[PDB]
Image: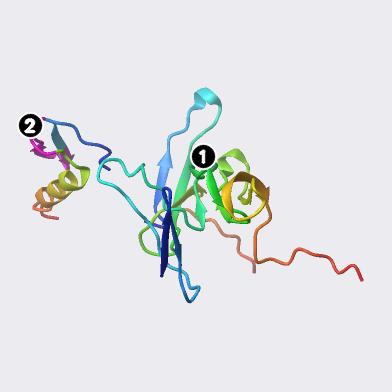
């Protein structure tokens, strides 16, 4: 569950001992959104076999 | 579908009277909109103005040992649309009268 | 998702033990908003042999 988003925030998800990371943009960038952050996290953790 | 708007209220009515789904959300918090339909969470989400005799169900919390209940609307003007009060009512489409004969 | 089971860690500080909550979609099936209600723990025998 992703609740909210904030400028210049790196998200780390640990599954089965491995970690994948995504860093959002700063204030000068676009407004971050939980939908895009979750989509990126899903497509990066989907590479984990099993 | 019949769609009409007044103030900040978008009235929806299906011509054949059948049911449908209803859900809305914005791109920041999904709080500024309230897609009222059938039953909802808590009475705090009720808009101030409504149509009289409008029936909405409220999901009670069995955590508090209270079951569900319903709230009905009556306009302050006595008819039509306008501000009014929500009071604990009976569920609709249910037999509720005793044959006095 | 409906029929989803999650456990809530109770607080013995308040003299209430643990419990569980289950989900049922408002649409009646599939995914969608719904209610979380106090339920029984899963994977446990819960019926009486009526015979």
Q: In which quarter of the image is residue B27?
A: top left
Tell me the subunit letter for badge 1.
Answer: B
- Identify which residue is drawn at 56% across, 40% down: B63
**Farthest residue toward the right?**
B101
Q: Is mark 2 on a helix, strand or loop?
A: loop
Residue at numbered disc 1 = B44
Q: Where is residue B68 in the image (x, y as percent from the top left)?
A: 60, 50
Name the foreground residue: A4 vs B83: B83
Please, what secondary structure does the residue beneath circle 1 have? helix
Kindly identify which residue carries mark 2.
A28
Question: Badge 2 sits on which subunit?
Answer: A
Q: Where B87 sits versus B95, above or below?
A: above
Quadrant of the rendered structure where residue C8 is? top left
Of B96 and C20, nearer the camera is: B96
Q: Is residue B53 left or right of residue C42?
A: right
Q: In which quarter of the image is the C terminus of chain B?
A: bottom right
Please give left or right for residue B74 compared with residue A26 in the image: right
Residue drawn 40% across and 60% down? B22
Marks 1/2 same chain: no
Residue C33 visible in the snapshot? yes
Is A21 inside the magenta-drawn segment?
A: yes
Q: Can residue B58 be seen in this view?
A: no
Q: Position of residue B13 (x, y in %)?
A: 47, 66
> What's the CA distance linking mark 1 and mark 2?
37 Å
For residue B50, side relative to residue B89 (left or right)? left
Identify the residue at horizontal 54%, vertical 50% (top origin).
B50
Q: Quadrant of the N terminus of chain B?
A: bottom left
Question: Which span is picked out in magenta?
Answer: A13-30
- Crowdedness of circle 2 by 10 Å Cα count: few (<14), some, many (20+)? few
Q: Which of B33 and C26 is in front in this view?
A: B33
Q: In this view, does B90 lie to the left or right of A4?
A: right
Q: How crowded is mark 1: few (under 14 residues within 10 Å), some or many (20 or more)?
A: few
């Amino acid at each position: 569950f992703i609740k909210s988003a904030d400028f210049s925030t790196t998200y780390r998800v640990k599954l089965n001992g491995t970690e994948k990371s995504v860093t959002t943009g700063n204030s000068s960038g676009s407004a971050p959104d939980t939908v895009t952050i979750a989509s990126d996290l899903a497509t990066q953790l989907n590479t984990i076999s099993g | 579908f019949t769609v009409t708007s007044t103030d900040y209220i978008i009235r929806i009515t299906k011509d054949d009277g059948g049911d449908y789904t209803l859900e809305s959300s914005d791109t920041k918090t999904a709080d500024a909109t309230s897609a009222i339909k059938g039953t909802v969470d808590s009475i705090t989400d009720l808009p101030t103005i409504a149509e009289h005799n409008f029936t909405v169900r409220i999901q009670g919390s069995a955590t508090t040992a209270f079951d569900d209940y319903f709230v009905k609307f009556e306009a302050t003007a006595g008819s039509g649309f306008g501000p009014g009060v929500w009071r604990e009512t009976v569920a609709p489409n249910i037999d509720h009268l005793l044959d006095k004969s």
